[PDB]
Amino acid sequence: LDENRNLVNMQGMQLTGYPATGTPPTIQQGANPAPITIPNTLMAAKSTTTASMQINLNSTDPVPSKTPFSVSDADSYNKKGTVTVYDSQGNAHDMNVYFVKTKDNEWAVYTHDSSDPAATAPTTASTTLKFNENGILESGGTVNITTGTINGATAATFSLSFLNSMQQNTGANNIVATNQNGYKPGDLVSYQINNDGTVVGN
Amino acid sequence: SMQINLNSTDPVPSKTPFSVSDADSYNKKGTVTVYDSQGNAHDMNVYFVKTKDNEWAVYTHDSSDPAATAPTTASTTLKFNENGILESGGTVNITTGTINGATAATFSLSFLNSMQQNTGANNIVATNQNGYKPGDLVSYQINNDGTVVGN
Amino acid sequence: SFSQAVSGLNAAATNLDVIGNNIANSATYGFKSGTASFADMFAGSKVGLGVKVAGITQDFTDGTTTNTGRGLDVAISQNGFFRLVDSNGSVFYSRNGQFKLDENRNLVNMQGMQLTGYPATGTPPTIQQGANPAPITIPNTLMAAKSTTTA
Amino acid sequence: SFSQAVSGLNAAATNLDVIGNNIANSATYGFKSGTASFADMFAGSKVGLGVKVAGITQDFTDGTTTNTGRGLDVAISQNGFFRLVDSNGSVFYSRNGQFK
Amino acid sequence: SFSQAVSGLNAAATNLDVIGNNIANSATYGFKSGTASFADMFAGSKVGLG
Amino acid sequence: YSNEQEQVLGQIVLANFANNEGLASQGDNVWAATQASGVALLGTAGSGNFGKLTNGALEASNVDLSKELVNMIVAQRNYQSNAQTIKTQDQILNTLVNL
Amino acid sequence: GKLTNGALEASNVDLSKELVNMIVAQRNYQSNAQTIKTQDQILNTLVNL
Amino acid sequence: YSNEQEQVLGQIVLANFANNEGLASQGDNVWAATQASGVALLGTAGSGNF
Amino acid sequence: GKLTNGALEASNVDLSKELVNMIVAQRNYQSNAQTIKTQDQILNTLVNL
């Protein structure tokens, strides 16, 4: 690895290969080979556009006792989960998702941003998950969610998904999977060459 | 040139106004060593103070000049867009002080490619300048492309 | 026609010298082994004119960390290089962490090269992570007292 | 060529002499161990001319304190050195506390 | 190579010295026993030096 | 200090390079940055792209004696093979001159 | 530091460390001797041409 | 000296030439300055081109 | 310097450092003999013309 960040041999000839273009970068094989370079260029942040939360629900859960909803009161809801998303500047938004059982196989989910101190607590249903005769999610698996505006950064709106969520006689409500496509800025830590020839920077 | 990365989560310093002695009065301090006409080294200190989200006042001082006036006015203002990219205020013409009668150097300090996002903390990515001091011949070489270079 | 045999003998001698040097510096804290890299020198004809040494490549893999114990001793893990300056201001880098304080109380290694770093200034002193690196000193002067201003 | 191996042998011999001095001095009140520090001798060429002994560093770690029952025997805990004078007035410093 | 066994021997010697010191203070009012804590020394390679 | 208070005198700076193989060794276990190695990137231990510092310890050399001895054997054999080639050319030239 | 009366500061030489270092040093010395032997054979080969 | 004070007596000078190859060897591991090598530049060790 | 009674100053010849120098000087001597032989063959091929 020379001073200009190119992969060269002992004599200085530059190694060539298919370059990566786009966001997220992928190898475009339709282009002519170009010298391979490894810049330190900090990686910018990606505001979230798609988030997913797969969860399993208990059938035997009783309905919340203390109507109405309060984000402060624990006994006011059945479950609470946290998903970390990222805005245009990479700031962390901690979406708390609240599960309240309304009727049989019907679960209202509320969304509240806890990272923004001036955000109002939701009072109306964000979505109503409907589970069929046996866990099988029926409707309401996808909802548009808008972040708060924190420290002048652009609020990131995204589609949050509950696909493949199930509601059966599970012992308790616990989160199975949470994923999101956003990330915060990062600096180059390492580089490697895979057995398929791809150069990957971590 | 000074490429820096700033954190968007930094609180505004409490101690107004900015004071060089007061560490609590500014967010970040950096140093760049420039050279005047004769060759004396001027350690220009650049101070970044956050005022409002997407706004950073920048002050400059000369740490090599004992007679340099205390900075009381903001030298410039960096404004970053909602995506964290610098929009305006990235270039400013700055003049150093006079040491032992040497002519002060007026140079353009540029904060190009500086970005404000959610990093770990305020870190200076790179600093550079095109001035230097007197140099004596140490070695010579002939490179691969035939160019003769003296170090 | 010894064009090839002489070059091969020279390359073998260079490789053997590199191996012997690696053997000799086996107990040199901060030493990295070296390996010669060879290349052929075909020139117009297909007869294979000879061989040449394209260079000597270091092996910058971290060595075993041995707790000698002496406090000043500092071992470095992963990437990084200790920064030193000689008496003439030139900048050098070393992985050897065997340091001592000289008579002027300046952190130096066995060869007297002054260890550098970010100095501290002010009252109380703060690490000037921006200030250009300076030689580190450990003065023995008595520490003054600060009048109580906040309790 | 020969110089690199000669320097390596000399450095190994110096290390072994330091080890022998330490091991012969295992029973010596106030003695401090020694360790040889080596440095390479690159000069212009990348071939690595050899190694050299940069110096011998003492290890001033406070040793175990052993009682003897003599009133003139005193040991320096932590840092500090006994100051002594010879016949000519020259000054010297020693950690050994056996006085008569 | 040798460094691994050297580190192991030094750790064993430290443990032996700690045990001997604890035994020597079997009758020492207000004394609290000591125990050495060990940790591996992996560095880059998967060999796990010492 | 003795007044139940401490001071900070300095912070050791670390250097990282784009090209480790480009550093030219000047001897005395010391490296110098040149054109091929690029400019030194300065920082602190444990932050950015720098490893932390171990106190009371020294980093030994990464020279394994077994590999060095085996490579010495192989290089000796290669040197003797090249010497045999030289002898072959010597005999060829002697044969031609004796004509 | 303070002074303790009626006692002496013993040496800080730990014997096991010295023995292990001696073993390492001797082996290093033997490796360098092997290097000298190899270069001696090289010079003999070149002379006997 | 014996009075616990050192005194300097002189400094060794180093000479560098524009053309080292032009020096006329006089034997006894000794070189002499000539017109081809040019006038010797004097200085101190560790500074400039010394 | 000081005088120590009941003691003798031994020689300062280290055998290891000497044997190595003996090997090196042997090689130098053999190289010079090889040069002599080369000049001898030079004179031979000139004479036999």
Image: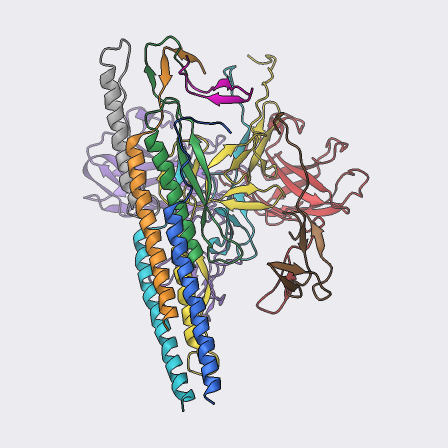
Chain colours: A purple, B red, C yellow, D green, F cyan, G orange, H brown, I blue
> Which image quadrant: the C terminus of chain C?
top right
Q: Which quadrant holds residue B56?
A: top right
At horizontal 35% and vertical 52% (from top left) the residue drawn is: G32
Region rendered in magenta: D77-100
* Whether residue A14 can be seen here: yes
Give the percent coordinates (x, y) of residue A3: 53, 57
Decide which of D68, A144 is in the foreground and name it. D68
Q: Which quadrant holds residue B92?
A: top right
**Magenta segment: does it hold I48?**
no
Q: Which quadrant holds residue B65?
A: top right
Is residue D25 found left or right of B112 in the rendered image?
A: left
Give the percent coordinates (x, y) of residue I25: 42, 59
* Whether residue A191 can be seen here: no
Give the percent coordinates (x, y) of residue C137: 57, 30
Q: Main secondary structure of the magenta part?
A: loop
Q: In the rendered view, would you say F89 is above or below B70?
A: below
